[PDB]
Structures are given as structure tokens and as C-alpha cells.
Length: 289
Ligand SMILES: CCS(=O)(=O)N1CC(CC#N)(n2cc(-c3ncnc4[nH]ccc34)cn2)C1
Image 1: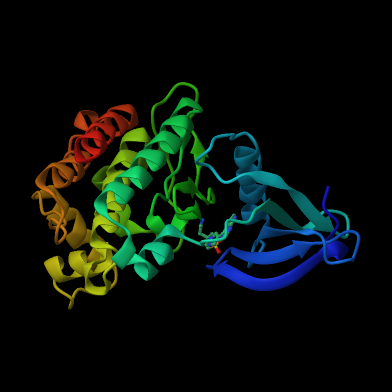
Image 2: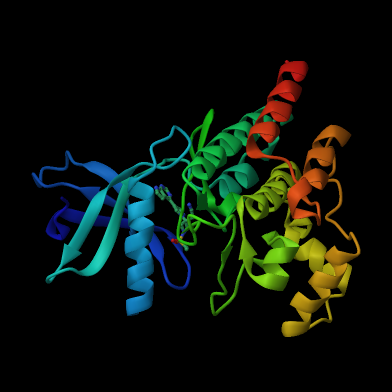
């Protein structure tokens, strides 16, 4: 539904290997009245990455929720080459950058509002049997000061109809410091591993994205900054197997840290549900108010 000739590039909003997102104006009348949109494209579009991208687009189109970024459409040139995903543009960028840049004005009650919205989005995913696999504040977007949305679904998988986990090992770097132990050891991803990652997101929020307090920084100190290459993963596994954990962030109340530590249960089946997480967070919010 979008013609590429009418997409006007404004700036880059994000870039990894395999993908990037741009701020563009969609201006079919060419009179500078069109709306600004976000445009995701692949960076090294192998056929495998293209099939994954088409599945990612279908997943996002199937999702309709206040805390999930809105699908708008697709754009392609020359037959169907250089597929692009069109999404609503959210003006405050990623929650990671937003929180870092406005930490002095964002209090704990606001952090818990964001936490509750992220839980509701994840519960919605879970009802569709979708496993996100990449939950992190860098993949959460800020629509306004009172509303956040899960913003990227590049790694999201649909569970088989007969199993409660999905096994996958992607070649390349993996956000291992957000991964549940069974995801590190067995490449097993589930609603429960998303819950483990959600605990890491909650940690991130209460660190306010302070430099040396990031999960990678804290875990690398705990295993020794000398560890190199593959040993990193091995040592992380051993650390988590012995119940090594990220510390309580400065100023974090004990009850919030306790939500984190319960998400970080080595026993997959004893981690809370996203509905229970939302319930506990919302009760704490109400107590604070
Ligand atoms: C895999 C690296 S990436 O470039 O594809 N990636 C997605 C990313 C993280 C998230 N979410 N990103 C999205 C935006 C963004 N900003 C403003 N409005 C928006 N609408 C839809 C996306 C969006 C900014 N960064 C950075």
C-alpha cells in the first residue's frame, strides 16, 4: 500500500546487523503534508533473513494492542525486492535512551507504570502463543510520557501447537545477558524465558541505564573481565547455575528486587506468569499512590 517513490528519508532511528529503522515522511501528494512514519528494512538481505522478515511482518500485523507498536503496511520495489515494513513513528524513541536522558524527572511510580504496560503487552503476546525472545529496554518504545510499547519483533517465534517451547540457535551474537539459563544451555525459548528477560528489563529500568550498571557490565565483572570469547557463555552458565544474580539497583525497594529475583528462577516452572507480574506491580503502584 506504500509506494517507495513517496517515502522521503529523514534520519536513521536504529541500526543493527541484519536490520535498521528510518524516520521517513510518506508524502504521496508531494506537498509536505504526509505523515512521518518508521520504516524497517534488512541490512544484508539473504533469502533466509527475507523469509524471517516476512514472518516478522505477519506477526506484527496480527497484533493489535495499546502497548504494541502499530503496523501500517509494506513497501517494495522491482517485483518484491527490498521489502520494507511501515510502522507508526513514536516520537520519544527507545525507552533505553528516553530513560537515560530524562532520569532526573522519572520517578519509581512512573517506572512501575511502564512495567505494567510491558507486562500487559507480553501477556497479549502469550495468548497468541508468541515467544518474543528479545525483551530489553532497547526494544521498548516511548509514545508519550505515559505510554510505552513493545517496538520490535525481529526474533519472535510462534510455538508449535504441541509444545510449550521453541528450540532455535541463531548464528551470530545473541543478547546472552538477557537470556534464561535454559536458553543458554539448550537453546530453549518459552513464555517462562520471556519472564526471565522481563526480570532483566525491570532491573534495567531501576538502574536508569547507568553506564557501568548494565547487565553486560555487571555480569562481566562477576565472571572476570579477562574471560574471552566462548568462555564468556560457559562462565555465565556456571554463574547462573550457582545462583549468581544481578545486584539490587541503587534505590530499588526490596519488593521490586524480589519481583526480579523471582523472575530469575533457575526452575523454569516456578517463574511467575505475566498476569501475576502485572497484579503485583499494580498493587505496589496503588500502595505508592
Ligand atoms: C535490530 C536493530 S533495529 O534498527 O531494527 N532496531 C529496532 C529499534 C529497536 C526497537 N524497537 N528501533 C526501533 C525504533 C523506532 N523508533 C521510533 N518509532 C518507531 N516505530 C517503529 C519502530 C520505531 C528505534 N529503534 C532499533
